[PDB]
Image 1 (cartoon, rainbow over the protein chains, first blue to last red):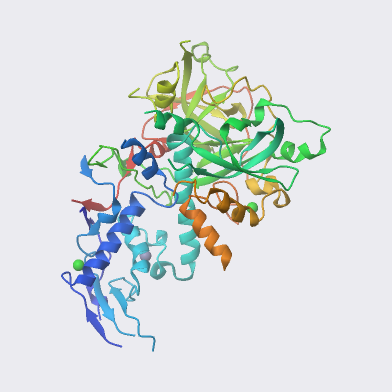
Image 2: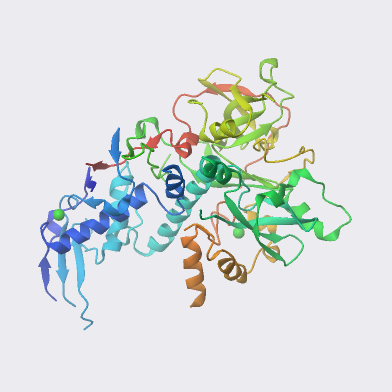
Amino acid sequence: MPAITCVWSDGRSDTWPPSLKPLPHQDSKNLLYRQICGRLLAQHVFGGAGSTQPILNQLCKRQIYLTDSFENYYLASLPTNYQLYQRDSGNGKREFWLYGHPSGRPFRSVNDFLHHLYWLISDLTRNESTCCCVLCSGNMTRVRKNLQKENERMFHECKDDTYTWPSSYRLGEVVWIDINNELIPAIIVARNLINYVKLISDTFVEPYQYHCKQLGNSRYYFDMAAADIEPWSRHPLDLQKQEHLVAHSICQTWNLFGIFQPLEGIDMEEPKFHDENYSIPLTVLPTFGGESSLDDHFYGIFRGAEKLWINDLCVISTSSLPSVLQKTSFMYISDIYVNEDDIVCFQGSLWTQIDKNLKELPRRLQMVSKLSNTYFRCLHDKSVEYVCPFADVLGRWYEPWFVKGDLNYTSEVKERTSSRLSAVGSENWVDDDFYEYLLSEIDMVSAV
Amino acid sequence: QSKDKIIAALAKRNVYKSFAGLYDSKGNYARVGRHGSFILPVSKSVPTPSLLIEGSIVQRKNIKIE
Ligand SMILES: [Cl-]
Ligand SMILES: [Cl-]
Ligand SMILES: [Zn+2]
């Protein structure tokens, strides 16, 4: 039963005060309050919206040591200078009020306090403007809550596309569908993990069901397997086939997304909490939102048909590049940012791959090595990286089994858009019925 | 009312109507650059953003756990 304590607290004792009944530490309801705070805090700091790490963990089960079942965590103690109360209602239902907030107002539910609690342990700058709770944000609370949730999901979408389930197609990508020998242009709208040594290898190759939307049509196609999908660059599009022109238009665009503030080195450390039964390192949810620099940094970028991320692997032009680096197979992306000349730059290490027919590799490449006769080497000193403009990024690098054949169909990416939906066009996106159908299609099979 | 229950059920499946890059972040000046330019080395001084995604490095927290 891991016990959580707050390092610091903004609580003020002199905010303490239709009757109110103090609930001390020993009270069974104070305990329940602190048990809910601890569980949900733990699931937030070591999880957050969109996490699929428990799925990978339970698949792998076949410094400080800690259990990964966050339902057991609990607050050892309320943050200093906070006081809990029971208030009688005429509605009747009891309410549990927590005083201490500098504004002098109570948190009238454990759910409202949680957002402030999460800010107390996450915001290392103790900046009151980054909290989503009702008492710091008032009317902006829903907007801030929603953005935070979106950002948490973006982080886990990034982690899954580059660490957890990287050998896969990505949300919003334009692909080729192959059904009954028909090449259908489509866009990935949604995807879900399939509920289940060789278990881990099959999941790494086919982790997802894909649910697509034909481009130039109103047709939905649910429950697609990667074996029936090919990257857009595998086959050519037809100039005279009128319905192909929606896919042609989208695959000429690009848009940055997921702006964030890089973290300073003093706010980072080596993994401190691990799984007590398996020594798996816990995933710590970063809170990038802050204040800074003339460089804007971004989680990722749509390049025509493909989605690209930080921590991802991409192909780059080797033409203008010293003789020492022309064996470069891909860049391992470290950072994506707009410099002060307004140019999108990719920073990362350069590698070569050798098909024969792991400490220092990312998990994605460690798995490619176990599952193929392919070996990876960095072409340069471990302490430097290289920077090329977006102009010299050619596309995604795919695992060696991902594509029988080659990708020679480059497209002219020359139009910036504000959004993927803006480039797709709302008339070419899905309607709300899609998600009604989807739910029925995956109701039993999908992971939870 | 029935739409809220479907969405809630899809969320248990990690399925959402929204994902990174779909909608405008606000609700711009970046440009592509020059092809065939020079590709220059720089210093890997502090942990880059990519490593927080990998998990090799984590952000500090104001939390003590026993
Ligand atoms: Cl207490
Ligand atoms: Cl939009
Ligand atoms: Zn707050």
